[PDB]
Image (cartoon, coloured by chain):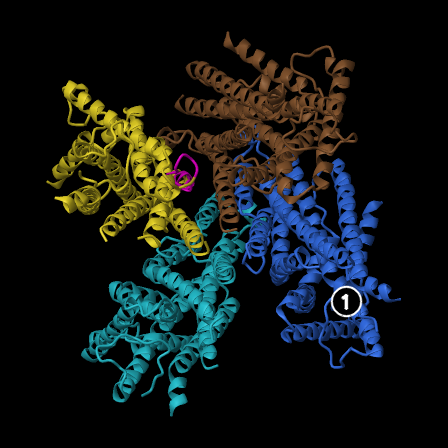
Chain colours: A cyan, B blue, C brown, D yellow
Amino acid sequence: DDYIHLRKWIKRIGIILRISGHWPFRLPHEKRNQHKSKFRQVYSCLVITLGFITCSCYCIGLCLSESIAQALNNITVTSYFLQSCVCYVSFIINSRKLETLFNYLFENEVVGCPRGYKMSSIKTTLFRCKFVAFSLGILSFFGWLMWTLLPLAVLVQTSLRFVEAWYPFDTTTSPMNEVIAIYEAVAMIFLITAPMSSDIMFCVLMIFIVEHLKCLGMAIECTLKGDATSLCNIVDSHVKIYRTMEIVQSVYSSYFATLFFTSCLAVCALAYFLAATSFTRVPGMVLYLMYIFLRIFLLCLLATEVAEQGLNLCHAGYSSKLVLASDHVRSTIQAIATRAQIPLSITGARFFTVNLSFLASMAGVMLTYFIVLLQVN
Amino acid sequence: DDYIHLRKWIKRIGIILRISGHWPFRLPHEKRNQHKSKFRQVYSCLVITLGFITCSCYCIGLCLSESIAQALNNITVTSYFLQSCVCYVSFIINSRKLETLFNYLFENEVVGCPRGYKMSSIKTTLFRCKFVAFSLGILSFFGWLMWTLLPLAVLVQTSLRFVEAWYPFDTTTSPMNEVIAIYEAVAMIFLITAPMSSDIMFCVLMIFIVEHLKCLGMAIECTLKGDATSLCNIVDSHVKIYRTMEIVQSVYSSYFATLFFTSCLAVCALAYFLAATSFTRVPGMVLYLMYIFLRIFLLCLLATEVAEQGLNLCHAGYSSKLVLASDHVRSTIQAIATRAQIPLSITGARFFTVNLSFLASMAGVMLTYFIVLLQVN
Amino acid sequence: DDYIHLRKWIKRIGIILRISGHWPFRLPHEKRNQHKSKFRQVYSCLVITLGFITCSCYCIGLCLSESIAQALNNITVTSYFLQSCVCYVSFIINSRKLETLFNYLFENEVVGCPRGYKMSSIKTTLFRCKFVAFSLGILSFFGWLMWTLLPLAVLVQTSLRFVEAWYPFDTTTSPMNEVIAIYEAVAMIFLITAPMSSDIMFCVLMIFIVEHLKCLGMAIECTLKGDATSLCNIVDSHVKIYRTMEIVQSVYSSYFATLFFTSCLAVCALAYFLAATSFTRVPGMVLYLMYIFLRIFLLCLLATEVAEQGLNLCHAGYSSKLVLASDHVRSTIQAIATRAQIPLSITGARFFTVNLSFLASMAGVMLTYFIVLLQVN
Amino acid sequence: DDYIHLRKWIKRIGIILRISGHWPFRLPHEKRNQHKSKFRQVYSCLVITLGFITCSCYCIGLCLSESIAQALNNITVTSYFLQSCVCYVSFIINSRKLETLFNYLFENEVVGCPRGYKMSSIKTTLFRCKFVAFSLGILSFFGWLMWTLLPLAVLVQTSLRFVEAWYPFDTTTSPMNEVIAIYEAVAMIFLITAPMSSDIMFCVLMIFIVEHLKCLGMAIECTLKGDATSLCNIVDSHVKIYRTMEIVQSVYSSYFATLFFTSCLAVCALAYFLAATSFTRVPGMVLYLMYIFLRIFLLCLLATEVAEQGLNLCHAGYSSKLVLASDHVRSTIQAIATRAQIPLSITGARFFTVNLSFLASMAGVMLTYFIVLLQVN
């Protein structure tokens, strides 16, 4: 039933990842080696070299510092573009571990859990992944729309760029402004759709791992309430969880680091420009602020959820029946517990572990720095 | 003897919770389904919709920002009202887990502990719960009295509101001021009595859980000094402790988060208004400052006490007799210890774990922020 | 041999504690109930009521705030006096646990350790305790000397008080200044000798506990290299270590809290007065700064040493022979390790755990606060 | 094959350490007691007394504070020289533990690991140690070259000192400036080559320990997939790892502490001089900034790598076969895991544990302090 619909959803996950111009890899429903086709490779290289030249144009526009007052006005845009750049190279560096992750995410049936839990698990996973995917997609589309379309609509020269960008031609005359306008429009579309897609895939992985942990705990209490075989299957599922989390930690680290850094810098610049300096500008800046904050909050929440479920897995099979089991179960449960005491955490290039606590600390120091450097100055 | 008096006290706990206008649930001494009576439901809905309209009136008075200098003068009052709002919805969202918690708190006799410890336990619990309940009740009553009655007594128009609030009528003329005065008086009474009641119930739960932990440790050393049955009873009591703490964590998280946030913001505003700006105002503001600080300190203390008693439970039954026991006791004690190494902590919406250490850190950053932003500016 | 000299040293420890006016308790070499003698009790009550009236005089001199600029000039002196006050009441509240601690510290021979380690242990303990005791005593004597004697010597009225203090008589005329000078001199002598004595006793306890831990580790490796009896003796010694550390945590908490707080406040005031405001004053203030810093550093070092030795005790008996021992040793060593994973830490009223890391954090925030509030202002 | 080349490399490590003027100790390829030769001892004493007199000259030049504005201009140079001083005495205090460390680092073959892993291990270790050694050597040589040669080349008096230094002769006249120029040139050469050499040896030790940990994990999974003997060899190798890490912690602590402290102070001074105050100066200061940052980053990275590999060693041999092994393996693996839960961390004089997280925190507070104290002031 809905198990087929979930597989259609994770097929859509691969499809939207191929649309955004990442390097294509083998999907689970791919048995003809179509992931090395000419069309997809040409599309990928075209979109990534367009993103690379646009980001370099904005960076050299930054290095051609017009003044300090507009410099922060540049930062944020280049900030977001920088993220896209990093994300691209990451998906080309580790394009086999992604195949491994999708192969895990296609079939993850832990054996022994009761069915009444399994169907509710499928329902809850479908609901939450639909919610997060639709939310981030709508927010990204509205972000592009507000950041690109509106100043064109003020005119109908186009003079729509929220900050000016370096170009070979001067972009001053009436034909050139229009050409650079349409070029920047399609460019920023294909740039904004990349980190949204990577974020959506990370959130899907986190949701699936959380539900697999809860089903593993249910299987543990089920085999305790009931000799060797169930424990072997449970231990295999747990070590598979750990290896999958290790792979996810291996791929996402640099992207998380650059995301956190350039995001807090862009929010500081955005507050500096919105606070004391002078009607059309405020919708775009408030929408970009919400686009940063909601994304960071979703990442921190779905990163803390898996660690909480691991420490919940620590308290599994801990009842009176444990005092009446054999020595074999009494030792294997001990082994599972002392392995579960290690926290399954994701860190950004080993600089910081992404939790809700790190979000609170970063928000505290960012609020502090912004409010002092704008108020006493 | 006093075991009956303690049950009368926890009946009073339910009674004062019903008085403050929360949604009524089944008490342990309720065998006629009176918790769904018409009178109690009508009273609950009336008080909560009055609180909801008053909080919205103060919030729209805030959004109608008269000036910045009076804006902080608004914040604190709306701050406290905000807490009440959140608390209301929480007790209606989880109105069955509260029944479960009261059913646990009515009978919690751990089997095997010596009687000489049990009677002293009853005595100490009665003393401490009486102390905390009377202290918070007297402080809340004096807080309302000072914040409402005195500026009326300066007159006998009433012109008593410590900050003006938005209303449909202008409240300027002499009849209207009096009507809004009595309305705000009864409103703030029924608003102040809610978080005090929730705090008192949380403190009662924490005290009972702490004493149950100490009795569990006494039972562990008793059954070690003395085969299977006592260990099963001890493990069952421990896992019951853990499930109860999980339920308490599940209900109180949003309230703790909003409490900490809007409380530190209100204290910052209160210091800004008391420090450098201009005899009647100072008693009310110092009493509100004490009302914030003592409440936060009581919460942090009774939250750290249970974690300390858990880590104390880690060092249970650890003597020479452990080296002479069977393998069975030697494995079950190991299991109890490695489960007890997990800290039983309460966190506010998983943002921060409420300890004395978090109170010290928050007080440090609050003192820092206030003293810099008032002194160098 | 030197074992007798060490007992003479810990007798001197009790003697200097009786000299400073604490409430007398039973020493180990006291078999005639002389700790309840009339002379010692009269001396104790006289010195503590003199300290209590002098501290209250300085506190009411503070509350009679002459100006803000001299107010910080008051703080530090009252700061130190405050510590003395707290220390007094603590030693009268728990005057039996101190007897228990001294009874432990008199005989602590762990059985089974090799003799070549035991004699070197006695030597190292004697050396380090002599060092710390002589250092703190000389520093305290020079602190009193510089803070009291020198401005009298500038004259030979006395006009020597580094900050003026409230008194019933005006202290302005020539007879009164001299009388208050000699009164404050003997008062500050008997006040300064109290926290130095408590600190010296704490340092002696920490040194003895550290050396006992190292000898316990040596005994563990000795009985592993060599069946039941040695393990029972080792476990008994370890749990005795834990109970002693619990008692030390129970007594010293309030004193550590007030010490850290009023010490960092006094150092901030001292820096404010020394930095930008105007030859005789600078020796006293630099000596008081060193007296604060060296004391705090000694406390943090000898507090971190015991935790490091506990985590060193975690890695005990971990060799190839563990793989060839019986199941009995293999389980008891596991129990010792999983108990040793709990850190033996001292905390100040459960607000913060005194480590070198807390000293680094406090020094960082203190340096920050001082340098900003003096420079940008 | 390359095993001989690696031994030639670690011979070069000893050779470059002898060149920089440290006190010579016995190398593994030294069977004639040549480490106590007259030539090497004379060279060592000459270079260290030259470093000692130059550092004291710069320190007394600092204490002869010309003005505040040039004072920070002094700090950095004295800062670096201070490190050299400390490093010298450390290598003379513990000149036997270094022999022990080199004797470990010469032969570290863990028995039982598969050969296909061992050859790749040798290859990866050779690559990474070559990389780090060549990088730090080239950076140090260019640092000396820019900091000494260029202002001489501006002339061809010499007037090349980036900050003036105290000397017995006035250094003002034309002969004296040249003599002090050549003296300071050879001095700063022999001073800069010391902490680079100590850093290179620390990095080699960290790389070898990391690879030994990975090979130990491979040996664990190999002996689990395959009775007593392999486990004894594995446990012996693990405890040898722990003792080696303890020795490295014992020697490097004071050097790490002084490095972190005087390095962040020098970077703050360097930013203060580069930011707002006035073409030749900027290459030297940017090269010194890179020389500080890259060194600190390399140290933090190779310090965090070993802790990550230890927590990776925690998850060793955790498969289904563990559920089918004997009780003996099931207990020894448990012992290995609960010992591996202790983090193998290096700390700087027990003030702070050097991780990437401490680098992030220090960079945050340094950025904060610099930007506030330069901007609002």
- Residue under pointer 1: B188
The secondary element bearing badge 1 is classed as helix
Q: Is residue D347 magenta?
A: yes
Residue C235 seen in this snapshot: yes
Residue closer to the observer: B177 or B246: B177
Vertical comparison of B60 with C259: above or below: below
**Which chain's residue wears label 1?**
B
What x and y, as percent, mark residue D97?
A: 29, 27
Residue closer to the observer: D333 or B285: B285
Vertical comparison of A130 with B141: above or below: below
Question: In the orientation shown, which residue stands out farthest toward the bottom?
Answer: A156
What x and y, as percent, mark residue B250?
A: 61, 60
Residue at x 72% of width, y 68% of height: B163
Magenta span covers which residues? D335-351
Amino acid found under the numbered disc labelled 1: Met
Q: Is residue A216 left or right of residue B176?
A: left
Vertical comparison of D251 with B294: above or below: above
What x and y, as percent, mark residue A23?
A: 25, 71
Residue D236 seen in this snapshot: no
